[PDB]
Amino acid sequence: SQHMAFARDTEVYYENDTVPHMESIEEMYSKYASMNGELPFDNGYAVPLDNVFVYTLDIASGEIKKTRASYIYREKVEKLIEIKLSSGYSLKVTPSHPVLLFRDGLQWVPAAEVKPGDVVVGVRNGELEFHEVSSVRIIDYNNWVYDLVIPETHNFIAPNGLVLHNAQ
């Protein structure tokens, strides 16, 4: 099992107490490590979070809800999968990481099984949004990979709407 999933430049959205923030997951980790400290955890390090919340998607009902984030994790990884969207945006995640696609309806699919032509799923203005994949490949990454752990539902919604799953 793994507790890290996302490249360091993955943008996140969250609220601390009531105050919204958008920044990269490495920027978030640095901010809260300074504030809260780091705990050795698994094969890397974790920063505990107090009063931090995200938006999350229930894929069965389509309901968007608010739920807490428990901690941010990081560990170094050699190789990631880069899923590039026709927009030029790229999702860079570990190869087994579940990615939300629309195939036979909404389905979580391991990143390395995502194909050009698949549609990655996000939600915006309450509605599902579909983004065609332009290319996939393994990349040499060799750096910190992160997760923002969401215990209730195991996903958080990024600023661009993509529904990002926690590491497994």
Image: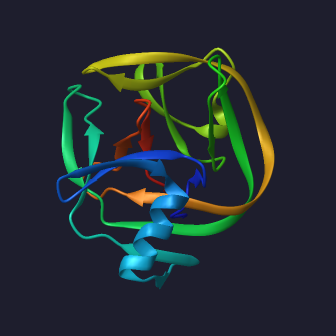
Q: Is residue 8 visible?
A: yes
Task: Quadrant for residue 43, please give it.
Answer: bottom right
Task: Quadrant for residue 51, please give it.
Answer: bottom left
In the rendered image, the residue lying farthest to the right is 140
Query: Is 39 rendered above or below residue 69?
Result: below
Q: Is residue 104 visible?
A: no
Residue 95: give x, y in percent of width and height.
66, 47
Q: Judge by depth and name the residue closer to the eye, 25 or 156.
A: 25
The structure residue drawn at horizontal position 41% and vertical position 39%, both measured from the top left corner, is 158
Task: Quadrant for residue 126, please give it.
Answer: top left
Q: Judge by depth and name the residue closer to the eye, 104 or 99.
A: 99
Q: Horizontal placement of 93 versus 14: left or right?
A: right
The structure residue drawn at horizontal position 64% and vertical position 14%, both measured from the top left corner, is 117
Query: Is 109 rendered above or below residue 4?
Result: above
Residue 65: give x, y in percent of width and height.
18, 39
Count of numbered circles on the image: 0
* Image quadrant in which the N terminus is located: bottom right
The structure residue drawn at horizontal position 78% and vertical position 42%, both measured from the top left corner, is 138
Q: Judge by depth and name the residue closer to the eye, 97 or 54.
A: 54
Q: Horizontal placement of 137 versus 167: left or right?
A: right
Residue 46: give x, y in percent of width and height.
46, 75
Query: Is 67 rendered above or below residue 157?
Result: below
Q: Horizontal placement of 33 versus 94: left or right?
A: left
The structure residue drawn at horizontal position 40% and vertical position 17%, both measured from the top left corner, is 129
Residue 26: give x, y in percent of width and height.
54, 60
> Coloring scheme of the render?
rainbow
